[PDB]
Amino acid sequence: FDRDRLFSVVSRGVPEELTGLLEYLRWNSKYLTDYTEGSTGKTCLMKAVLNLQDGVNACIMPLLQIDKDSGNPKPLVNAQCTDEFYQGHSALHIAIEKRSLQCVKLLVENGADVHLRACGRFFQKHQGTCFYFGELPLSLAACTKQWDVVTYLLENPHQPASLEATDSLGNTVLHALVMIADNSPENSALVIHMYDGLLQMGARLCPTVQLEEISNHQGLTPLKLAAKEGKIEIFRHILQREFSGPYQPLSRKFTEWCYGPVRVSLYDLSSVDSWEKNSVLEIIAFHCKSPNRHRMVVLEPLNKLLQEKWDRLVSRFFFNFACYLVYMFIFTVVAYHQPSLDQPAIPSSKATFGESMLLLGHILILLGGIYLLLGQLWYFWRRRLFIWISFMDSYFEILFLLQALLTVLSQVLRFMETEWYLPLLVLSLVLGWLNLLYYTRGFQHTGIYSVMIQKVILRDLLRFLLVYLVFLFGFAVALVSLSREARSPKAPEDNNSTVTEQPTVGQEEEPAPYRSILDASLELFKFTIGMGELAFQEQLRFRGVVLLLLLAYVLLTYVLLLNMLIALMSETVNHVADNSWSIWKLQKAISVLEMENGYWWCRRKKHREGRLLKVGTRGDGTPDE
Image (tube, rainbow, N blue to C red; front, side, top):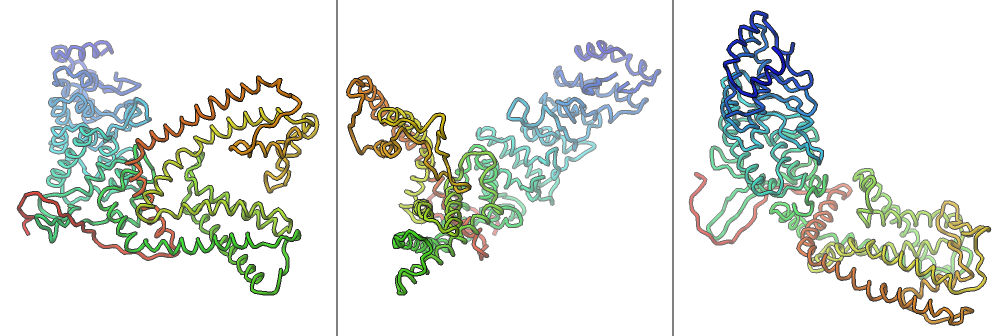
């Protein structure tokens, strides 16, 4: 025909102009595309299915039969849209999207396929307007609760829907329902109960297929994916799953030796038996926190398991802290009792218990330092943290990398045998004694306390630093200009006195050389945390402007801004406090789970969980013994 003829006749939906269609494109025996859209592929059944018009698509038949004399009839009904946006898109998809019933019934009776991928640019996520749909009419049919067309798209006179099927990214109905599900409890409840009916007739019309056993292209089960995008509700459903029908082991919360007062909820710990893939904390942690990573530990197998594994095995962490604590004591006693001679690598201060004991402490201290380097290299090749271009997370990892770097440079320049090995040693000292608070992860009120200081310290570290270093650097330079004579480190000379003058060792120079106030400027920076006071010079109190000026900076900064960040980190205290429990159970589970995951080369124990419950409520019956 012509284009506006077909567009008009689907604008009306009047079959009286469809009356001449069969003969008018049967004498010519005309095909379908030679006519339909070159951009999309929208057929008459498509351009009439798009508009709903009371759900009654009447043109299921005439281009199917024009496409039967020209022979494209299931090709009439299953012309996937070749638009980029609407891609892979059939009319059964629209028939679901219009939420009607004639469209599904005489679209399927027009021969519509069921297993067909709709890999649409409209139909996948960006974080923008286009989001993932299901990409296959069963998948989005379940994702839209439409049990009439899930049921229908199974029960078709041509095709039962493949339950085990996958989709465009590998994202099956598991990944479609889960991935479309967010923390909206209407969305959550529909994507749980609708999914459960898909497992019910999903376990009745097509049983004998384990759908959750399927992993995606990334190798993630729906437990791994639902436990990967941070949906504690769905994973909670997965381990909450309990099918009261033939027969039993679909469930995950079993109740054997159970009782009215005394419930015993048996679990499975497939979360911890998932060794052929990643563990469950691994895949909550990767990808971490799509809304929330810390939330998912509090659920009963993960929390109770993370408790009992510590209290049964990993409360032996005090051996690790014991060896490390004795290590750091060795570091600080070799550093303390070092000889005051200028020449390093002395043969012996005295052939006695002292200097020989110091040689033992030296060989022990680098002999454990090489183990710290081995541990971080296992962390790096094996763990591949830190993140690519991201922030300093995690803090003590790169603090450990900087301590290890500075102490192997200490070993290098000590092997060069110059005196400067020692300030590096004091830096290694303050980063290890600093790193003692990583060993506070263990026990109860101090582990809760340790996660508290881990939280507020991990947040407010750089936040107070950008106040501190910048305000104090500005006003610091203001005090270096005022006042000190012999003000020539700069400009046309070496201004910086070749700052970081040590080649390939670091910031070892006289950097930022002052106006003959270098010692007075490290000394005023040492005054800047409130020590020394009140000198004047050849300004001689014409700098009363500088007096009131320091009253202005000390005014707005020293008191008037000092109360700000304490107060809003107390707002963090107003928010993070319950979240610090999630961070507590998590960091306990990282000390534990990472501890057994690293332990060179470890043992474990894998047997079915069971959780005692002493609660009181009625309810009798049995699972038929």
